[PDB]
Image 1 (tube, rainbow, N blue to C red):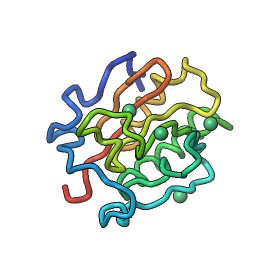
Image 2: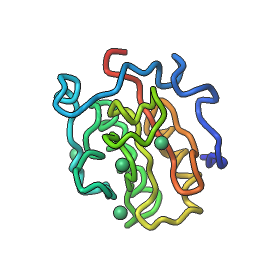
Image 3: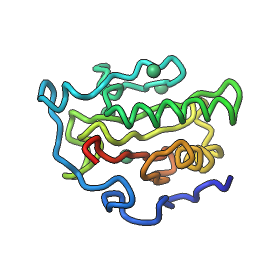
Length: 152
Ligand SMILES: [Cl-]
Ligand SMILES: [Cl-]
Ligand SMILES: [Mg+2]
Ligand SMILES: [Zn+2]
């Protein structure tokens, strides 16, 4: 398996194109009907930074949970004793551009639990192999992973 390079994305097309994660559907706000279709992730093998102390980053679509949970298994296989870590998920605080998949339960920013940046390119490759529809080495400090919408 070949690690991704900094700022590389796989597949090598824009995130919201049909062969990647597909179009945005619209921001999800708390207590909306679409919010009620999100599912919380309390997987003990994933560390959630949850800096807002709201648990919002745990709320994600079922496809996002499926791929994230597969990635959590893969991380523990690659580096025994290390866990997947989520630093950003579903944003309620307005940090991202319009049409960001972070507003839809469809995107996560991730690291390893030890914050060893030398692992991040490989972490991104593991996310591709775990089935995320788009993976991007988005900053020196994290990998961005997203999924197609349930209606796909
Ligand atoms: Cl779980
Ligand atoms: Cl943390
Ligand atoms: Mg946040
Ligand atoms: Zn991101």
